[PDB]
Amino acid sequence: TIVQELDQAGITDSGLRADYITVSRLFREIGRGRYLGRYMFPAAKRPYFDAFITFVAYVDNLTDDIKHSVEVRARRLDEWERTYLAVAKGPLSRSEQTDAAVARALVHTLRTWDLPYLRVPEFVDGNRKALTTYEYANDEALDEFLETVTLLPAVWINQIFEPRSAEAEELCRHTITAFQLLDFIWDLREDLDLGRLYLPMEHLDRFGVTRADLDRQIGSGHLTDDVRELLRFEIGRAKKHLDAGRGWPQSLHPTSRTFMEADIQLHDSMFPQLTKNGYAFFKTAIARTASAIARARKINQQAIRGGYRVRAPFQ
Ligand SMILES: CC1=C(C[C@@H](C)O)c2[nH]c3ccccc3c2C(=O)C1=O
Ligand SMILES: CC(C)=CCC[C@H](C)CCOP(=O)(O)OP(=O)(O)O
Ligand SMILES: [Mg+2]
Ligand SMILES: [Mg+2]
Image (cartoon, rainbow, N blue to C red; front, side):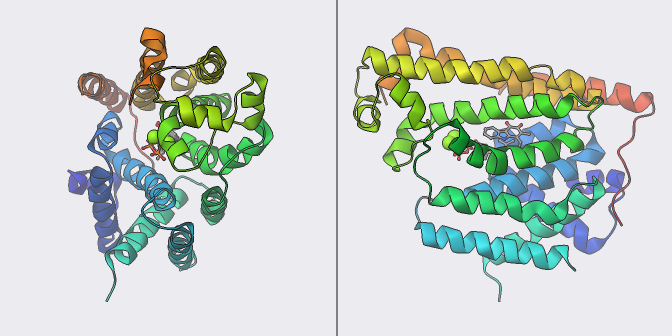
């Protein structure tokens, strides 16, 4: 339980403990599948994993609340950022209550791990900019999204994973880039329906494809050779990044390897789903997790018997 994990982490402040408890329950609500990854980490690290993942998912969710206007979503980002900065520098609606718990846990997590907690607004600004960006002219323009929304939190959580070599950050950047590019491809139909194109226009031009072509053909039952070749190209670009980043687990502390090995393997499993049966994925509309938890429990206890201990909390 989070209470025993907080005990093992040495987090004793009753106000802070309550915030980590709130965040852990929120984490479970934002997705049980992702929440279970916490059990691949040493018990005393799970409060930090909870707080960091919840922060990224919580803020990204503010940005992708497609029920509401871009103006409303922008206001929510401003609200969370104001609350974060108030906490960082030392009746409530439900969103105000969660904003504050997420912020308080995150500040403590970031300071515990020697991360630049005052730069969190750069991540929020990337999300604010993404709200009003519906197209990307080329790779350089898409990098404005990737280097703020995607990879800034990625290089931060890399430190929480306890890198053993300097190559870890580049492997982290390749791997999470591949994950993000696969998300764009997987979600192409939904994103197109929202008026957003995350495939750079230069790539479309290269294969003679228009945005209208994609809008009309994805989910239509058929694909022209040009559209299929564009999809093949984008899938191959994601594959190349994943292959370049695949050594990331070995560059991390042993207690972090099982989680990222499982996550890489999950994304590996997306490639045949996208392409099989002649790209049928684009024409029409638990076991791995249990095994990884089993493997992680062996590795983590080994590491403990070898003297491993999670660092002391910021206080
Ligand atoms: C640590 C991590 C991360 C890093 C994140 C916690 O900042 C991640 N970012 C993503 C963007 C799109 C699709 C997947 C990811 C992921 C992960 O799967 C992951 O494990
Ligand atoms: C999954 C993780 C460790 C952190 C969350 C980063 C981001 C939220 C994942 C994208 O996956 P996803 O749930 O599909 O978001 P999306 O709907 O596409 O904007
Ligand atoms: Mg998506
Ligand atoms: Mg998605």
